[PDB]
Structures are given as C-alpha cells and as structure tokens.
Amino acid sequence: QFSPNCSAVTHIFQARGIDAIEIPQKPSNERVLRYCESPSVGTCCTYNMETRMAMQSRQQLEGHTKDQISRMSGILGSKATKFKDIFTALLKESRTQFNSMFIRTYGVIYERNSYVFSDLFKELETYFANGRVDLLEVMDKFFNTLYQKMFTVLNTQYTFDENYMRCVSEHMKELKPFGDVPDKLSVQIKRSFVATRTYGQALTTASEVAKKVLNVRLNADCTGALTKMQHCGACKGYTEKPCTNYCVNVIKGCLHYQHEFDSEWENFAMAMDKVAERLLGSFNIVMVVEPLNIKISEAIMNFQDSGQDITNRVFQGCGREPILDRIVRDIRQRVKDYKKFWSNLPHSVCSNEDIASSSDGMCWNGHTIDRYMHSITTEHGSNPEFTGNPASTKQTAQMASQLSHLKNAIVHLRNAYNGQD
Ligand SMILES: *[C@@H]1O[C@H](CO)[C@@H](O)[C@H](O)[C@H]1NC(C)=O
C-alpha cells in the first residue's frame, strides 16, 4: 500500500501509556511485529510498543470479565443464602405455630402424640438441610403410625397392650383408613420440599461454578487476535475504532471456552424459571397447609364411613404476599436477567470505554478502514479471526467439572419440576 501517517496517531499511543520517547516519528521499516502487520511500507509501532499494548489488552479483557462474573456469582450466591435462611426460619416458626395451634384445639389427645408430629418436622427440616431423607418413606411411616393409633382408640372396648401391633402396622400399609387424603397430602408435601430445596441448591451451585470460571486464563492465541483488533489500527496510522462485529468475533474467540457452558447456562435459567413457577403455584408449601382443616375433616369423614369395615378386616389376619414468594420472585427475575449473561460478555466488552468499538461506515476491520466482511459467528470450534479452534484443550479441561456440575443441577431442576422420583 502506502506509508502510514504516524503523526495522526501519536496521541493514541500516549493515551495507551507509551512515552513520547518510544514513539517513532517516522514509519519503521523493520518487520518484527508479532501481531500487527509489518508491510514493506513500514509501521508506526515498535516491538516494545506492541508488547505493552498486548499485555494491556489482555489485562483489560480479564479485568472486565472478572468484574462481571464475580458480581453475578456474588449476587446469586447471596440470594441463595437468603432463600435458604427464609425457608429454614419459616420451617421452624411453623413447627411452633402448628404445635400451639393443635394444643389449643385438640388438647391433651394431641399433646400425647405430639412426638409423632415433631419427628415428622425433624425429618422435613433435615431434608431441606442436607437432602438425605426419603420424604415419601417418612410420610408413609407417619400415617402408618396414625393408622395404628386411630385403630386403638376406635377399639377402646378391646385391649391392645400387646406387641402384636406389628400385624396392625403391616396390615395398615395396604389399607386406606382416611381415604386418599394422606397419599394426596404426602405427594404434595414431597413435591414442595424437593422443589424448594432444589431451587436454592441449584442456585448455589450455579454461583459456585460461575466463580470457578474465573480460574480459566486467556491463551496466547487470544492475545494475538485481541491486539490486532484493538490496537493495530493505530500502527497503520488509522484513528478509527474497531468494527463492532469484528470486536465481537474476537472476544467470542477469546472466551470460546465458555461455549458449552453458555448453552447449558440457558438451560439452567429455563429450568429455574419452571421450578419458580411451581413454587409460586401448585408446589407452594402454603397451598398444602392453608386448607389443612378441611383435609382433616375429609379424613375423619372417611374414617367414620370405613371404620366399622376396617376394624373387622384388621381382626382378619391378626386376631399480603409471603416473604417466601418475594425471595422466589426476586431470584426468578435475577436468573431471568442472567440468562444470556455468557453470550452477552463479548457484546459487553465491546461497549466499554477501553474499546468503544464503532457500530459502523469507517471502522477498523483488522486490515484497513473498510467494511467488515464476516458476520457474528455462532459455530462451535471455529472463528473467522482465529486459525484453528479458539478454545484450547487446557481451557475446556478446566471447564469440564464446572460443566458437569451445572448439567447435574439442570437434571435436578427438571425432576423437581415434574415431581417424579
Ligand atoms: C498526518 O497526520 C497529521 C496529524 O493530524 C495531519 O496534520 C496530516 O495532515 C496528516 N497527513 C495526511 C497526508 O493526511
């Protein structure tokens, strides 16, 4: 082509931290630049100027992504902690209100068997804490104990002080003294606790795996493409900003190790929104305790119609909005905000003061001040600004465990949404 105009870009180099002593007044005829082009017509940059601007671009990109990722990780992590603390306190406050409510209502006959209810609450609190509880198993044993006690006081005419009660326990497993009320209540409680715990646990893991992405350093191939995009325009005497799509393609390649992680992050956000829909609707733990007295009345009505029938079959064979909804809505909206977080990073990087790429028109496309031919790439394993795969084997190996944990939480969210187990 023709010799570049180094006088038009002398202020740009000084703005990048390069002292005026290092800045060549006339184009340099040496051809030793690693990232910019060194044509026969010369260049306005030296090897030391290129190295300074190279490490500057890598630190600006790593700084911008570190601030974005850690702030998202911190917010989601603290909201998960607030969610768990609210439900944990709501659980303990319920055990007391439930005990006080039934003692004033049913009296000593409840307080005599209050241990059956406190043991159930203890299992429920333990499940939400560590998840090592079979909820349906605990619920079935809960009603089985109620089935046994309801059989003794019905037959106050007889004496059942014997430990032949195992036959009653074994026979009450297949019988339905209260109708379908215990089974319907056991499933709705199990679904609610699984969805509630998984919602907070998946949000915590997403915050943890997001924080671990900070451990992945940019590779040498990223440094080359980054400097050609952001700084090498001034080395040809050009003052225009890089083209937007050109900048986006470069940052996408620098951050290409996040490709799979970005797509699964969207799956995580969609599964979180489904569970949040359940928690605000059918699976809401308030929806199973608000109509609790009518469920008891139906159980008693079913026990008065089937009591004489079951006591004979046993002898045969024996002888204005809740704060829980507020934190769920808060998490749901913020997870909705961070849905496209990873694919938006290249667009976020290309919009700051450090790069400030031009949306055009006249912009630096890597070679000249002309139109950028390529479009924003969406491929997995290629990029127009990179020779081979922009993601190195070392980067994807660091992302492997974070990808596996994120996918693991998506399976639990989907299972919790359907409620099957
Ligand atoms: C080179 O840049 C200087 C600095 O603005 C300017 O004065 C001069 O006219 C430019 N030369 C050409 C040929 O455009």
Image (cartoon, rainbow, N blue to C red):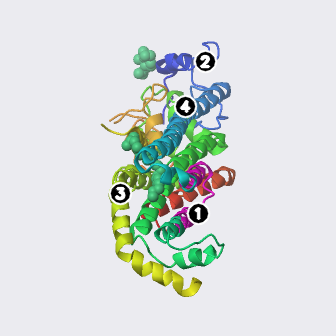
Q: Residue at x 37, y 40 (%)?
A: 322
Which mark lies nearer to you, 1 or 3?
Answer: 1
**Which of the two labelled residues, at mark 4 and mark 3, occupies the earlier sequence position?**
4
- 71 relative to 300 in the view: left or right: right
Amino acid type, callout 1: Asp
> Real-space Cα distance between discs 4 and 3?
38 Å
- Residue under label 3, please give it: 282
Magenta span of residues: 117-145
Element at label 3:
loop
Residue 44 lies in what quarter of the image? top right
Q: Which residue is mark 2?
A: 18
Which label's residue is closer to the chain start, 1 or 2?
2
Q: Nearer the viewer, mark 1 or mark 4?
A: 1
**Separation (CA) of disc 1 from disc 4:** 41 Å
Query: Could you tell me if the residues under marks 2 and 4 are in contact, i.e. CB atoms within 8 Å?
Result: no
Residue drawn at (43%, 41%) of the image: 331
Q: Which residue is mark 1?
A: 134
- In the rendered image, which residue does mark 4 sit on? 67
Rendering coords of residue 130 (x, y %): 62, 51
**Can you name the residue that lies furthest to the left here?**
320
Give the alpha-carbon distance from disc 3 to disc 2, as whole Å: 63 Å
Which sits in the foreground, 308 or 207? 308
Tag 4: amino acid: Asp
Q: Residue at x 44, y 68 (%)?
A: 183
